[PDB]
Length: 330
Image (cartoon, rainbow, N blue to C red; front, side, top):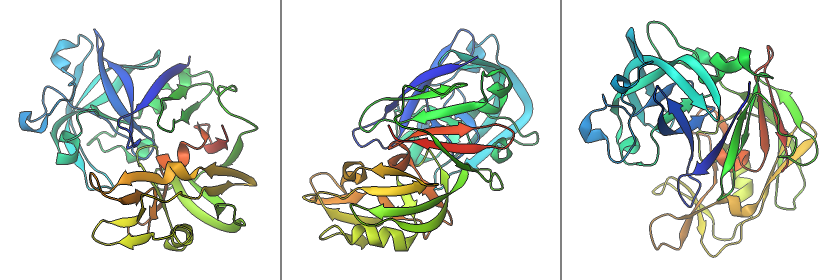
């Protein structure tokens, strides 16, 4: 089997991407944030505290003839941005782009933090990291990809995120028309539960490439590119007037600037992020200070190849017995 679904930016900045997902019988379609940095499929639901729902579409398990309470199971998750959610668990039929999994754990939110409530466009998350990170207790649950894997034509999914435009998540096949050149594969460590890999270096603009190992995670659920402070300083030093602002929470730059590109290494290959992809617009409405799309990871504990980086590439998440990542230009 295969599946193919379009993923659409939630706003004009590509702050996140939503993909429609069919849950239950008859189908209830929710727009989920596919997140290769976490491993829970959770949704706003008929059980979510009413004051914490503000425009999201909800899953109502009582209206699904295939929903079953997973008795005793609870979940609770906290994300790197400080947001969180928790609740109980149903199993139900879940379909993405024509690919169907029966018995998928659908984690129903009883509580969500304010940032989720405040984003009416995201009805939940669909985790695509390794199932060892799934938070369901006392019986850990598998991700949608893990459950689908054995049925897929090939044990892979691909992320093809658009810049200010829709893109595609494919399951079970590699669309050879969706990228240019060849795909370069690189080793993955699953030791932390992430799609963790080592970039071979970087360049700023037309500058020379610096060969240096940068361990980080391919994370579709993180907006920006978070890299070591040395690398980030070298980037922003090429932008007149750019500075790190403690009050804003990162590097800002004059909105009048033209940003240089940023290149990252994948083995001997190179992925170029155009400068425009690094512009996240005014820090507040009407400001002439703009927020940068490359930020320091120094306070995170891990480097994160988020959407800014991933949307410059066609990315293969290879879930074979020994997982690997593939990157191609497009």
